[PDB]
Structures are given as C-alpha cells and as structure tokens.
Image (tube, rainbow, N blue to C red):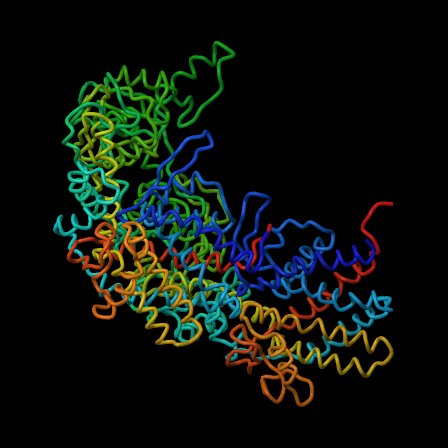
Amino acid sequence: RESGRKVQSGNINAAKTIADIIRTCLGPKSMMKMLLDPMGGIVMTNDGNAILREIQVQHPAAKSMIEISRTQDEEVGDGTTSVIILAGEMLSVAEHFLEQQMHPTVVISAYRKALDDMISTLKKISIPVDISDSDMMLNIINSSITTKAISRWSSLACNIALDAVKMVQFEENGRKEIDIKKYARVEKIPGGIIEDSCVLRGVMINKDVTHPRMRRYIKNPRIVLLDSSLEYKKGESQTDIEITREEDFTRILQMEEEYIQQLCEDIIQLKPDVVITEKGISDLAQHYLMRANITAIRRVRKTDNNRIARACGARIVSRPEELREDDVGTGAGLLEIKKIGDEYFTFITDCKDPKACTILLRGASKEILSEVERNLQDAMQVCRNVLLDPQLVPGGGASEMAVAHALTEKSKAMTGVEQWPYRAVAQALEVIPRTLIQNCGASTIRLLTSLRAKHTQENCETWGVNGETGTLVDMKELGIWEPLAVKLQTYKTAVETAVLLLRIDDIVS
Amino acid sequence: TGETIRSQNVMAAASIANIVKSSLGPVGLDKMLVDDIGDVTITNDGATILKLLEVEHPAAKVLCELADLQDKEVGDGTTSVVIIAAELLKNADELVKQKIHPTSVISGYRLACKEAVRYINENLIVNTDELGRDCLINAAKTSMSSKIIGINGDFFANMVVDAVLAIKYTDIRGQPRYPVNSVNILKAHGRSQMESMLISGYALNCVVGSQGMPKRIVNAKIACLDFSLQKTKMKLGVQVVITDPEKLDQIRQRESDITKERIQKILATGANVILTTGGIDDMCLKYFVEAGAMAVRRVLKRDLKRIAKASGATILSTLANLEGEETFEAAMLGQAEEVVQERICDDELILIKNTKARTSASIILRGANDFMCDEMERSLHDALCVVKRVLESKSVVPGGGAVEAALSIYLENYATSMGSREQLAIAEFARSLLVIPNTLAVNAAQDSTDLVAKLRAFHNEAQVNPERKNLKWIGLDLSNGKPRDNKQAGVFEPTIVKVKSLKFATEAAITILRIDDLIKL
C-alpha cells in the first residue's frame, strides 16, 4: 500500500531502476546486463525481455511496467526496452514537480499531446517504405537483424522472413491489416542442408506427427483431421449400456463399428490414405484405420490439425456426420512424409485459404537452424510491422530530437502548464541520444546540444545520432530504420504506461 | 481503545475513505488494489474497489456495505457515503471528545439529515430533457473520450443522449415507453462517422444467411434462436436392408430429407425468419432457403434477444422444444412488420425493420475507425446509463455540487435558528456536506475552499436553481470547481439518489458512534 509521492517517487523507483542498465542494454552498441541467478548463475542480457522475468519485483508499478514490456513483447518483441524506458523516463521529471503544481491530470492530457506531436512529427520523418521491393524492406529488415546480430542467417532468413510474412500476407479482415504471422512458423529439422531454410505454403507438421506408417508419402490421398470421434459410438450417434447379459453384447457392437463405419463410410469417400485423429483416436479406432488401408495417426493433437487446418487449409471436422475433402485435406492435397534427419516430417503443402504458409528452416543442426530461426524473428516481426505499416522512419536522435524540440516548440506553442510535461517528455526523447552515446563512450552533452543544433538547422529530420557510429547523422543516409510501425507502436505503449502509473497516486490492497 | 478505538472507527474509515475520496467515481485516479498480498489490481470507482478491497476493521466493514447498500439502491452517492460517515465522524469527532454526548447532535444531525432533504424535496426538475443530466450533450460528452467524437460530444451527443431520451423504442417484449430498458444501438467502423444514425428496427449483429435465403421478407415471422440449429449425426434411414445399392443412397439420403421435410414443416409450423444466436449449419439453413424462409446466424445475444423480445409471442431464444433436426413447435414465432435485409454502416446485416408487435429503432454509430466505435461505445452505453436513470427518475434535483454549498448554508441557516446544542448539531451537519465538492477538487485538482467557500459565496437567499449559478447556486463541474447553469454543463443529481446517501451517511456513523469499545471482556 502506497500513496502520493510514495507511489509517484516509487513509480520512479519502479521503471527507471528497470530502465537504468537497459539503455546501456539498448541501442546498436547495446551493453548487456550481468545477472546473478538464484543458483549463483549469470545471464548476460541486452534484453529488456529477460531482465524483468528474472529480476524480482522492486515496486508494484514495476509489475505494471513488466506487463507493458510484455505488451510490447506481445505486440512486437522489441521495444520492450524503450516502453519501460520511455514511460519510466517520463516518470522522473514531470510528476512530483507537477504534483507540486498539483496534478497527475494536466500531465496526462500533456502526455496525450506529448504523444500526438510525435505522431504529428512522424508522418514526415516516418515516410512510406515500399513493401513491394524486398530490399526496400530488407534495409529495414537488415536494420532488424543488425543489432541482435546472428550475422550468417541475418542474411538469408531475412529474405526468408521477408517472404515469410509476405507469403503469409493475404490477410483479409476487409481492412487489409497485416498482423499476420502465425501462418509463418519455423520448422525444427534435424540434419539436412544449412540452406533450404525457406518459406513453404501451409504447415509442414514438425510437432507431433511422425510415423513409420503414413506410408512414406501420401500425396493425392487426403490428410484427414478428426476432432470427431473416430472411436465407436454404441448407439446411433450415441452410446448405450455395457454387457451384463448374453442379450446385450451382440446389440452393442453393431452400432459401435457401424458408427466407425458410418463415419468411415463418409470418411473414406473423401480418399485419405492418412487420417490424422487428434480426438477419437484410440486402439480400435486407429486399428480400424490400420484395417481401413488408411494410416492410423496417433500422438497427434489440435495444434497439429489446426496447423494442418493451416497446412492444406482443412477444417478439422466438427461433424460426426458427412466428412468430405474440403473438411480435411483441402484441395488435391499434399501430405509429404520426409525424413530430413531421422524425424518423419509431415509436409502438408497446397494450402487452401492460401497465403497461410509456414517456413521450412533447415540447418545442418538445430543451432545453425535456430540461427535461422532467431534471425527470422526480428525480420519477420518487422516485416509483419512493415507489411502492417508500410512506412519507415530514421532512427536514433532523428525521431528523438525532431519530436524533442517539437514538444518543446509545442510547449512554447502552449507556454502553459502542460508545457512542463512537454518539457519533460521532449527530454525523454533525448535520453536515447544519450543512450546511444552513453554506449559509444563520447560525451553526449557536446552532441546533445549539437543534436539540438542538428535540430537548430535541420530539425533533426533524418539526422539522429547513430549508436554504433556515435555521431549525429542522417538515417536515410545510413538506412537505419525504425518504422512508424515499430516506434509509434513502442512509443504508443509507454505513452499510456507513464499515464497508467501516474494514474496511480495510491497503491492499496 | 475507547476514543482511541472510536477514532480507529473513524480513522480506518478516513483511511480507506481516502481511496474513495482520492478515487472519486470515474474521474478518480486508477488505484492499484492488491487482491490479497502478491496480486495487485489497478482500478478505481470507490463504489467498486471496496469490494475488491478486503476490509480490515469493523469500521470500514459497514462502509463497503453501506456504500454497496447505497450502490444496490442506486449507483451514485456510493463512493461518497463512505467518506460522509467519516466526514460526520470527523464533525462529531472532537464533539464526542469535547463536552458532547453525540446522542444530542446525532439526533440533531438526523433532523439535519431530515431538514436538508426538504430542500432536495423542493429541488427538482420535471423537464431536464433538452437540458439532459450532467448537461445533455455532456451526458455523452462525459461518456465520450473525445478524439474523433469530441466535437461530436455535441453532434452524436445530440444523438445518443437524445436517442434514449427520444427515439421510438421497444422495452422488453415490444414495449413503447421511456426506456429503463436501455436502447439497442450498435457501432460499425467505416464510411463517414457523422453519418452514424438511427435505423428503423433492431440493428443486428448477425451472420447473414442469405445464399438465396430471401433477403426482404414482408410480414416476417421471426425465429430468434439461442438454441442452435446444429446438425445430428444419424444412422441408416428407412429400413436397414440393401438388395440393390441405391437404397444405401436413399437410406442415408433421409438424413437431410427428414429435416428438409421438417424444415418445410417449419414453414408449416412457422416462421418467415430464423435468427440464431447459436449456430445454423447451411445444412439446416439451405432447407430454409429452399423453403423460401429466412435463417440468420449468430445474431448478437443482445441484438437477437432484443429482437426475441420485440418480435413477439414465443421465441427459441428463451425456449427449446426444437432439435433443429426437428420441425418447429411454433415456440419459435416472433413477428416482424417486414424484414428487409439491409445495407447499413459498412455492414450487410439482416435489419429487422420495426416489428409486427412493435416499431423498433436502433442507432448504429459509424466509426471513422474502430476508435469511435471504441469511444462511442461508452458514449453509447454510459449516455445510455445516464438517460435511463433520467427516464427512470424524472424527479431529479437541479445541481449536484452547489447544492451542498447551499445545503450547508441552507441547513446552516436552519442551524442558527433552532437554538441550544441542536443549533450546533445542525451546523456540524452543514459541514460534512461540503466534502463532496471538495473531493471534486481532488480529481479536478481544484482548490477546495476557493471551490467550496466560493460555492457558498453564491446566493441571494439560499437556493440551487438553473436560473442562477451566480446570484444563487446551481450545477458544478468535473471540469472546474465552478457551479454552472445545468444545461451548459451543470452536474444534475437524481433526487432519489441524494436523500439515500443523505439518509445513509448518518446511518453508518451513529451505530459506530454508539459502540464504545471493540475489544474483549
């Protein structure tokens, strides 16, 4: 239970102490944080991702800061640093002075217009990228893989992750938003070539579906996805009593297998040689498949068939009556059982609801595969964000100072009370030019004022400090891209978040 | 203990009464509520938090209870009646400690609790209508978080607030009347937002079943189904026996056909339209389209039951004698003047125009993007909540806040007149009245006396009237500490809402005021 400044200064004691090493942990020159595990261990993290998990809670507001780092991790997976940075970077200056001006409130609506002038600043500096050209994305998409940096597959997996969210973009809500990712999924492939780590349609099933008898391939015959009751039903659609008598025993087995029959009267008509039964899978049920010349598929689940629903594009059958093709194994279908390494890979290509496409990732080993798998992430995430938002914006102090004086100019434009948060929020922008230089080792001061001067001339339009060169430069020059996607999404979060814990003047039970 | 525990009876209140003062209704700041020990929850609305709060002391025991007792009756005067006991418990605090047996002043507080309402009694307004409650447009303008709907906090507030006020509206089961039944109103993002308007009928949220299901249906018998139309797994049909193969086709053909037979018994039993909040497989649905009947899917629970009420007679929403493989029993007969499946607000939806049993009207609030539909949502619902209580209670006092400043002086005048200590009793009751505008100085960050003392600075005689916010009292603001003539934005209070907390606020203290110790003997 906290109140007043004890919340507010405690809110400062929440995110900032989180965001302290994080700025060293952030930027392209990011300096990892050392951690000390409860075992006596160590974890070296540039992440705002891993720190909050391990580090124990230092303040109730931090538990709220953790989730907005989650929310940004949920939204992207990067910017988790900045959201707790930016919001916590807002908490230190404005509130207490403005509680001395007596308000959480004027700061909120200030934060809201501290939000918009950036959103006002962005549309110029955040300028449309062409999602058509891969390299026009790949410059953003190399900007995604360049900091986290697994360099070998930061090359190919991008073009893969480019194609990943591209091939998983049909996305139809009617508004053509592209959040669409899940269709794009990695594939854990033993052995094989380090290349042919690539995007294929549907979902080739690497999870639970690996069998000596699928035959070795089922191409034209269907993969049949059963939610439904492949096991017998003793009545019509239903079940009746067991055997206490000679009379009851013969009566039971008729409708039992007849249900399996009347299932596989309507199940066999659609031509599987592989029926994947996630539920209703049982010995006699799969033994029937064994006896039906249709592969008995066990140790398989909803994700599988939901991935197979995402693979051939099937709809996992919710009707015990009348199974068909477009139910399960849509199209002529391809179920391709390939051992690259010793795992049978269920390859189900030929996706219906097309543009739902996984990513076949093949290393010579899981690491060199996971090296594709991790580089894929930031790429495809930012690809998703670039395909979502077809814009890019210069990184570093460019967005920082162009909005900084803007908010400052806006603060002077207002010359009111809320100016003071604008005064506080504009500086929140500039800790990043600090952060970028607070990495490289020069004096950000000389450059801050010079980046002020970079605004004095150029309004820091495209000109930020680039963390790894530690100098104040055009990012359209350097091709360093935060998108209006990645940033505004990150900036949007913290804007709410600082308000949130500032909307807390009292913590209670 | 003693006055200590009696103070602990006051302290625990004012302690927790801070959280309901520091968070006052919606404008109260978010308060982090630890559920038990390690689980924290960010929330507000002291009428709420006290319940998620877990009461430590028998003092705040009744507070969470009386606030809820106030809240059970009506949602306002609730987070306050917490404070007001403590606020009186602060008024009689040193009194009980001074010379005072509070029995004197508390019975005087009673007459004060009584005498005061006799202004609230004489304080009413019959037509608040174009004045609204908390102004009119500001029923929604408060309900609207203002971005694209901000100036439409006039425009659509002339809509959604005037909607519940005036539109042809069907209460439960096709009932024209001033709604306490809310209003069916929807939101669909797109087109131009200003184009958001009323539709004549219920606005449906429904999966449209027109494959050749007839869109427009005149004199539409409506079946609104919460029970789905599903389908039933079925074994062999007529006989079992196969001499030649085509029987095995016909034997398994009556799986669809008996329902084809029974869904054209559904024509015979009846409906022209099948609305289903549950599922309709196109298996059943087609049987209607080849029957020439309407079958609509996943009609919104609200929207459907809104139809399922006005549609009239018996409806499958609240009933099931139907299997959906089965023919209807005509427990499914609702009735629509005409169903014209209608293109509205970037939606092709079945729009059931008026009713056979009623004339339905539903506004659809067209979002410029979802954010309107997100923010007008509250504007839909909360300005709905406002006018419903306004239609529920048409006797409502003019002014919320400056009432108390009057009620202070109004009662503080009646104080000096009575005499003795009960003169003093009435004056100390006229004090506690002034904290409710002061807990507005909490959230609006106003200056409590400059707020409240200047509130009291407003009078000729003592009165709160939309006539005079300066020569006398009226209104008050979440925007300021300033009284306002109620139609611009004054804070209206419902009359029934006030006397309750007034009544109740003294009713928490007096027993606490009686209990002389907490502890063992």
Q: Is residue B320 left or right of residue A332?
A: right
Find residue B154 and report its horizontal and vertical position in percent: 42, 76
Can residue A437 be seen here? The reply is yes
Residue ID at (21%, 22%): A273
Q: Quadrant of the C terminus of chain B?
A: top right
Does A175 appear above or below A167?
A: below
Q: Is residue A137 left or right of residue B347?
A: left
- The quarter of the picture where residue B110 lies is bottom right
Residue ID at (26%, 53%): A177
Does A476 appear above or below B240?
A: below
Camera-side residue: A291 or B285?
A291
Find residue B129 and report its horizontal and vertical position in percent: 53, 78
Camera-side residue: A423 or A110?
A423
Camera-side residue: B110 or A380?
A380
Residue ID at (35%, 76%): A413
Find residue B422 and report its horizontal and vertical position in percent: 84, 75
- The quarter of the picture where residue B186 lies is bottom left
Q: Is residue A370 left or right of residue B332?
A: left
